[PDB]
Length: 19
Image (cartoon, rainbow, N blue to C red; front, top):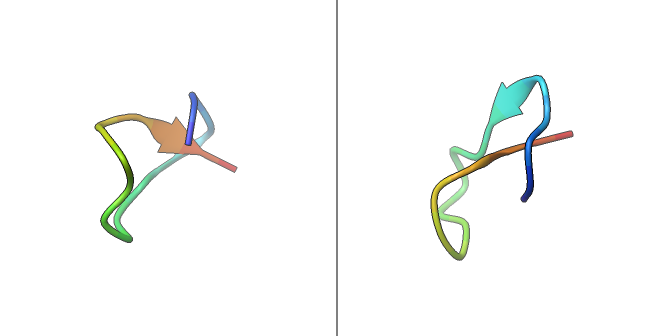
């Protein structure tokens, strides 16, 4: 999503963390 405490492991638009 952006830069959260958890990594986006749901097939995001790119490669970044999220809430």
